[PDB]
Image (cartoon, rainbow, N blue to C red):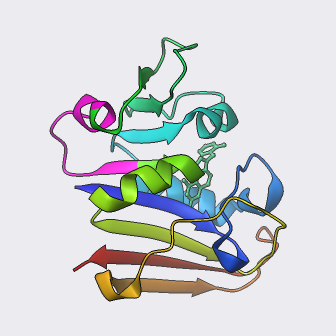
């Protein structure tokens, strides 16, 4: 199965991390947990923001342009990325904008972290119709000493 894991701001705004409101430690741990030991598919820029391959995980980069790092797998096609993951229980799509919008049609599960913070941004998350996504889990968390704004974890599944 294919899953997307994203962190969304107000108005479903998607964004490159490293800092911003997406460096939230507790969200990083939610990500690291759900993304541990599963093959990981990203974009160019989402790969640039990590700087290192995510360990114990095949890392796949969807890019129209050629590879610049042998520690990871570069592919050009959505279907090449899926195949490059082998036969695994769950594939994890990491971002960003263009990569989410390419993989939504084939995904069965969403791992959304809604953050209660606003960013002026022109990149958004794909508009999923609630008529084909069931909320299977939400976990609100207050603003914390390490977490600048509150945040709500959510899992959704296609019906
Ligand atoms: N909910 C949700 N979803 C996501 N795809 C991410 C995330 C938080 C950080 C993310 C995501 C994707 C890439 N990074 C940057 C990064 C990840 C791991 C280590 C170092 C790093 F810089 N949170």
Image quarter of the C terminus: bottom left
Image quarter of the N terminus: bottom left
Is 70 positioned to the left or the right of 151 in the image?
left
Is 60 positioned to the left or the right of 44 in the image?
left
Query: What residue do we see at 51% from left, 84% from top?
Result: 139
Query: What residue do we see at 69% from left, 60% from top?
Result: 25
Front residue of 105 and 68: 105
Range shown magenta: 80-92
Q: Quadrant of residue 26?
A: bottom right
Image spot of residue 141 (x, y percent): 63, 84
Where is 70 relative to 139, above or below? above
**Is residue 96 in view?**
no
Q: Is residue 88 magenta?
A: yes
Image spot of residue 110 (x, y percent): 40, 68
Image spot of residue 45 (x, y percent): 65, 36
Tell how many labels.
0
Front residue of 116 and 121: 121
Is 155 positioned to the left or the right of 91 in the image?
right
Image spot of residue 103 (x, y percent): 38, 52
Query: What residue do we see at 76% from left, 82% from top?
Result: 143
Where is 3 relative to 138, above or below? above
Q: Is residue 125 magenta?
A: no
Q: Quadrant of residue 68?
A: top right
Is 113 positioned to the left or the right of 116 in the image?
left
**Is residue 33 in view?**
yes
């Amino acid at each position: 199965m294919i899953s997307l894991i994203a962190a969304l701001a107000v108005d479903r705004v998607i964004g490159m991390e490293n800092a911003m409101p997406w460096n939230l430690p507790a969200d990083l741990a939610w990500f690291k947990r759900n993304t541990l030991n599963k093959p990981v598919i990203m974009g160019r820029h989402t790969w640039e923001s990590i700087g290192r391959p995510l360990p114990g995980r095949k890392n796949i980069i969807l890019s129209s342009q050629p590879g610049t790092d042998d520690r990871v797998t570069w592919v050009k096609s959505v279907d090449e990325a899926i195949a490059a993951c082998g036969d695994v229980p769950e594939i994890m799509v990491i971002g960003g904008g263009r990569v989410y919008e390419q993989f939504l049609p084939k995904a069965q599960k969403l791992y959304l972290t809604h953050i209660d913070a606003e960013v002026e941004g022109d990149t958004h998350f794909p508009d999923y119709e609630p008529d084909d996504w069931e909320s299977v889990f939400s976990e609100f968390h207050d603003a914390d000493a390490q977490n600048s704004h509150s945040y709500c974890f959510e899992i959704l599944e296609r019906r």
